[PDB]
Image (tube, rainbow over all chains, first blue to last red; front, top):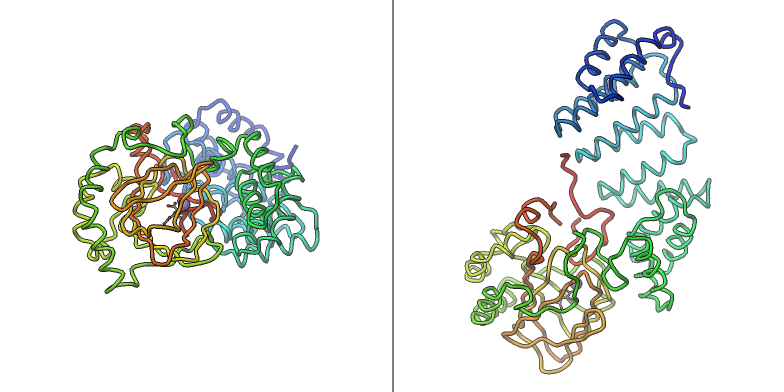
Length: 429
Length: 18
Ligand SMILES: C[C@H](CC(=O)O)C(=O)C(=O)O
Ligand SMILES: [Mn+2]
């Protein structure tokens, strides 16, 4: 269906097809060399060049090799450098280049390619949308917003652009404004809109404004396979792991860790209190837009399975104690952190990103009244020197209505049913 | 930008090829 052959490539269509035949039959090495031969004999042929690039792409998959893929990425660029490239081929080649650059994590590279694509095909909305995603992937939400604003100024009902514009609005705490975009975008059914991130954030935006319909969106998102359940809405999962909002120490099997935290809780407390008194800047304000009101800060010792060595200078005995416990210090999808919350705080219902961790809370300074935590349909309280354990992939909510501060220690562990193999392999979060 | 307690970033994992 796409027109990939310029005047000269039609005259060599038989050689080009012979080479492509080798690739589709999976004889990648013979195909690479066939297209190399063609490139040598016709160094200006765009189709030969693209064939070389595609073989390199398949070869990188075969060998699971980033270096080979970097080669393909340059060859996709060479296609675009050549004279007289058909438009369909130019677009395919540079689109694939950008997609593979992102796969390698070369987000700035991809962004340049996507900027080139939009300059070349100024009327192609899909490419402007793809450019916005490039900006989102490097964290440049300001530029992404400008991109989707442009798309929407010309195609107001582009559903991809709507859900992404809503995502950005929601991330900027423009909660009410984001709802119609997220909802209309999802309802559009356009390609790219049936994504759990948009169900997640529409339901959450609705919860925050007191809209009764949030859970209809959670229910639909579960029906469409994005959520394990209405209550458990994490999006980076291993399917099959036991799903329970509240866990006992014995259920987790990490009984030695719980015993050490409870037997040694006062030293953990005291180092936190010392940091609060003498190094308060190690406590950093929560910054994921999870508070309705109030004050909540965290002092993080491990994140993504990596010890923060300066932070551990502030809690050296605690860090020494925890090092005996690789189920938490090597939990590359969780953290180890102190968490202080003050009266007048309400943490919004929310879900963590992954079902691969369980969250332990050790009480350190717990006022006698006013502090509680809900996970799914059950609310509990903390106790000094005692551990609670919940699955924070379930929706949870916290209130602090005491008359003094409340300090806990948070210790994430790998979900117990994850094998050593998965624990070594899952990408960090 | 990391997803520590929530899911507020467009993507929570890092791209590092194969
Ligand atoms: C609000 C709580 C932290 C706290 O109560 O300090 C939370 O969201 C979590 O532990 O995941
Ligand atoms: Mn939480």
